[PDB]
Image (cartoon, rainbow, N blue to C red; front, side, top):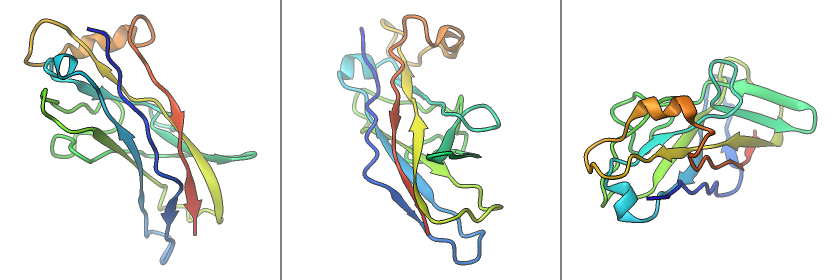
Length: 154
């Protein structure tokens, strides 16, 4: 089938910097419709502009910062981030992506924008687990989505 993951970031996340290393996660609400597409395993693959592989970047105006974004939500244990996929069933809820700020920095206050993709690798006709090798042609044929959320530094 032909399906994609939603991207809904619910307003800027409030980054509390109590001790600089406070750290917080920015939530992007991803969701794949049609249980038929989800039945494959609806593997969640996302990437932004982070410095490691591409995860997320907080940017406002001319201030873009690359942070190590590793997501949770429903991720398998902790194997997340770029190429961090989970096993979605036809009855699995939307997949939430969480972005982690460079807590080694302690950025300056501001409402930054975070760019994220987050498609699901669809296999069709299997109902078990999609092929991660399909990521090699990610932009080709696959319904890669992209949105921009927000991070309020505090």
